[PDB]
Amino acid sequence: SVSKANVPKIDVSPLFGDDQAAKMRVAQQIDAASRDTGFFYAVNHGINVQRLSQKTKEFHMSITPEEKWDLAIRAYNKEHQDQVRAGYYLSIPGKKAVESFCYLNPNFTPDHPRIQAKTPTHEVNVWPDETKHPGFQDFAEQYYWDVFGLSSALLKGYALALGKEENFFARHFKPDDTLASVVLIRYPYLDPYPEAAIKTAADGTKLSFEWHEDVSLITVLYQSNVQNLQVETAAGYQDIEADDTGYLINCGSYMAHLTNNYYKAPIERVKWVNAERQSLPFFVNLGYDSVIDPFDPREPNGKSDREPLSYGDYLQNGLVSLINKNGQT
Ligand SMILES: CC(C)[C@@H](NC(=O)[C@H](CS)NC(=O)CCC[C@H](N)C(=O)O)C(=O)O
Ligand SMILES: [Fe+3]
Image (tube, rainbow, N blue to C red; front, side):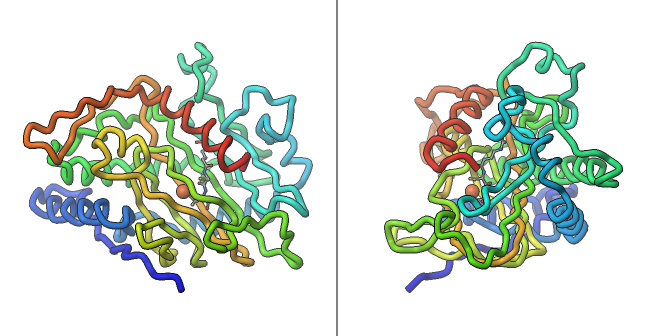
């Protein structure tokens, strides 16, 4: 028997406005959700998620093996030593079902001083041929900024929820240096589905991806309408209901650190489902040198002894660890 997680739907539209009290009522809901299962669905968010899913689908179903190699990250193509994060993540028929395409801040160009300095976790995006994928780069870049704008508003809600001024997080979330990423993930329908691509949890559940905590400040996730996600609670894993009009939001482990675990990063996993579906996370990362001073909302004086963590160092450590624990995606 598996229970269902309480994932409230929160109308986030006041966070784009100037009704301060209405923004506090949103913040209260974010607070409650963050202290309960850790998840909520952001609704009335203003993003055209039908176009997002449509363009994503066109890309996944039309890219060829030749293009995948040409775009592949270093884990699949030794020629691409600079592509640790951005690029195509190939499936392995018979062994690995999932495939995906990751891109970063469009402002990371050869002109960018972080690229000039070769700072870790910064890369220039790679893209397919425009004539073979008309409109795809423009769509993807536009979506990055559309979801950046939503995430900025959500971060105002999280700041208010923790008793802070509304820019406490968002001031560090900037288009010129954000390390945030979009991943366009395809989960395919396969018949027969390779058992090699299915993992079995301790509790016997068949999984496509084992338990993990997000490496992010927050995670802003769109998925098609196929239930798959679960969140761990003390009483076991609970199913997260699907909603292909909303964004599923949760705090990442950077948030857990800076709030002294008041807003924990939920432990989540992906059930195996033999169904064609899409999973499109936006990982809200800050700048490489962004440092948020920890605090403890449980203490009268709000004082935490936790060390201020530079975000870039945090991101580098978290992404290599996630690969080491749950395998190369
Ligand atoms: C909804 C999630 C569980 C989704 N998985 C994911 O988002 C996966 C596994 S946790 N994410 C990652 O591994 C981290 C990707 C980070 C990205 N390459 C970058 O350099 O910024 C899924 O649907 O599999
Ligand atoms: Fe996740």
